[PDB]
Figure 1 (cartoon, rainbow over the protein chains, first blue to last red):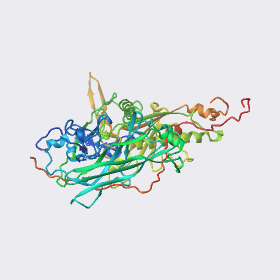
Figure 2 (spheres, rainbow over the protein chains, first blue to last red):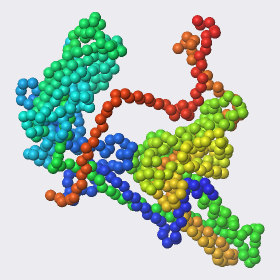
Figure 3 (cartoon, rainbow over the protein chains, first blue to last red):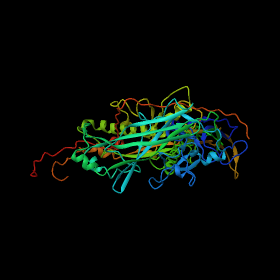
Figure 4 (tube, one colour):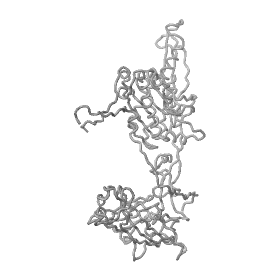
Amino acid sequence: HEFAELFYRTYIVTPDQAGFQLSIRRNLVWEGWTGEGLSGEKQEISKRNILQGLLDYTTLETNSTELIPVIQSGENDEQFIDPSVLPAQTVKQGKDTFDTNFLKFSENGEGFNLLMLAQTPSRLKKGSMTFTDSLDSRIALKQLLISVTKGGTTELFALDVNRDQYAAYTATREYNFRLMQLKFHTSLGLGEESTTVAGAESALLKDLFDLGYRIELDVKVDGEMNVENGNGDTSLRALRLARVFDKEGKEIALTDSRVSAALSGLTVTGVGYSLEARLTNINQLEMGLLIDSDVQKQGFMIPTLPPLVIVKPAMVEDDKTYPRLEALTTAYRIQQMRNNAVTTLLNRADTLKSYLGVGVPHPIESNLGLEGVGQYYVRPYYNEATIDVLNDLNNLTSAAKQTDIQGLIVSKINEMVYTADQLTGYTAALEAAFSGRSPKPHVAIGTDMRLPQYIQINGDDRTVGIGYDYTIARISDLRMKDKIVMTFILPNESEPHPLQHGVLGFIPEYLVDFNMIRNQRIGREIRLTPRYRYFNFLPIMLVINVINLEEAIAQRTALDVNETQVTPAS
Amino acid sequence: QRIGREIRLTPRYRYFNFLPIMLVINVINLEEAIAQRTALDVNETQVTPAS
């Protein structure tokens, strides 16, 4: 009847083909391939799906030619800061791994070449620079490192000075065709809650911070940069304690007792800085993100099932020992359309329990021990929960107990459907799969024949949620006692999709009628050989277990009181 | 030494910010509340000798 129809769409197949094969397309984004082949290279390790990028936040971001200083120990050390002040931290750029800490201030000696400092080992094998690098339209400080010292201990904090008022290299139109310089001098603050580098809070400013005060620093840094060679320099010029304010934004002089006591023995000294410079390649050399596609072919075969067989002694006719054909058709109808479908549904439930674990989704294109091409479009997701009606019920009058119960159950169903749609990304995958309509996901409700009397009411306008089309399916088998199975389905379209929950393999069969004499006995016989199988595709399912309803409706219970102890025990 | 056609997109875009006021509110532990009972955290008004 209706129940198996709702979950497994019927696909009529002519008897010539014993099965159907399905091919699916997919778009892939991936970094470079190992080594080199002389046609490019196809189908290498570490592929990713693009639609997974709609949910994830860094799978499509790339920086390829950022002019980042690269360390070559023993050749460019004199241009970097000392390694005993800030240890080198490992960074990743493209397919290349290297180390960078900070660039050292230049006062009176030679200026630094930003360009030569950015010779990654990737750029060597592609060839050394002759005209390759041209500095971009912007040069800007990324982060600025200061050092506060009190006694022997010193703690370093880098100021994220990028995207401020006055941290951008503005052009000064003199002495060269293309010359850029820096005019950075303003009052950058140190908040009363701000942390330090490598986590944790400072151990030199707690005395002032607990008083709710925060410090002002006067910084004077100037420099120049050439966008044709990489010639440049930058010098620190001033760094000192300037102003101290209260927690309310009014100035307190530096000579006050508390302020002087807190700031006694404190000095501020600059260490280094980093340049955010991108590389303009008008004659470009990059790999970007390569975009190629694949297909997977998966085959489904339709078996045969044990025959349903009749025999009767036939020299005369009988009608009440064996009635007309209706008996065989009834047996076929029941055996196929109900029991096996329910068995497959429960098996799918247990298998999902096994291969996902409760509440933890998996990325697109994960696992291959699951049936269906559904995993190629939507992130697999399983979740189960139980509801304790006795311990989760609100009541003030007995005349409304049923309303409160249905409210609890409908709220739980709403929440589960909402969070499943949120985590699976079923909706976004839905408009991605089919363009030309923008429908809303459909919710399938399957349960035993006792719950629908507590699910259907009119006190709540919402039953599975706003804009969600839903059908409640009743079933009379014993296996469905106190359980509701939730799954998204396609309500209208018939041919299989990875979004379809399941498709009913179907092959029409006719009966066979003739006399057969085995061991010398004569009697006509009737044959029926079922041809079908249930295939299931969509890897999403939500299941809720409802228990303890009867005593909850039987007994008055549970007004929630929390005597919040203005009685001295907490 | 392999010939193929290539197409590139080189974007030029940034987001600047002007108004220095932002308000952030965070909602946490919603599912337990929607699934669990909650009501009436009353305070006993100290009529039994303790004060």
